[PDB]
Image: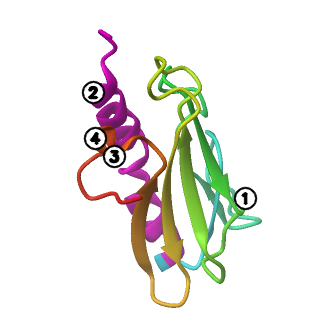
Amino acid sequence: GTEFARSEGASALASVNPLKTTVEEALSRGWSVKSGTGTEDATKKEVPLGVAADANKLGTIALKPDPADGTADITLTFTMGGAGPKNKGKIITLTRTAADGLWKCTSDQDEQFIPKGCSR
């Protein structure tokens, strides 16, 4: 009824959207990306995303595959387990397709709370 449903969606997207850059910069070096926080590992040539899975209390951030080397499709998901009733259990998915390097955003939210630039 009084849930902040549109702001929840915007907050979730804002937690994962910046990670596109992180991913591209790693792949441009020929390094892999791995989930979580920490330091670059020059032995395995892995760069962490730099963000904790629970950085945003609306939900959880995940990367697949983990680690990711750019030779397969990458997905970054925000799973809204901490959200109010309209958005609880919904998932925003950013996918980078390996064949062309393009990103897309899809959500299974109700259409009216899907953030700008994302589709069903």
- State which quadrant residue 41 falls in: bottom right
Q: Is residue 87 above or below residue 117?
A: above
- For the residues labelled 2 and 3, the Cα–Cα distance comes to 14 Å
Residue neighbourhood size for the residue with mark 3, other residues' Cα within 10 Å, grouped as few (<14), some (14–19), many (≥20): few
Residue behind mark 4: 112
Q: Name the spot of residue 92 as percent of width and height, x first.
A: 48, 47
The amino acid type, in three-letter code, at marker 4 is Gln
Q: Which residue is mark 2?
A: 7
Sequence-first tag of 4 and 2: 2
Q: Residue furthest bottom?
A: 99
- 3 and 1 marks in contact (CB < 8 Å): no
The quarter of the picture where residue 79 lies is top right
Mark 3: which amino acid?
Glu
Cα distance, mark 3 to mark 1? Answer: 30 Å
Asked if disc 2 and disc 3 are in contact, CB closer than 8 Å, the reply is no
Q: Amino acid at mark 2?
A: Ser
Question: Is 68 inside the magenta-drawn segment?
Answer: no
The mark found on residue 21 in the picture is: none
Do the CB atoms of the residues marked 4 and 3 lie less than 8 Å apart? Answer: yes
Q: CA distance from mark 4 to mark 3?
A: 4 Å
The percent coordinates of residue 87 (x first, y second) are 46, 29
| Amino acid type assigned to the residue bearing label 1 in the image | Asp
Which quadrant: the N terminus?
top left
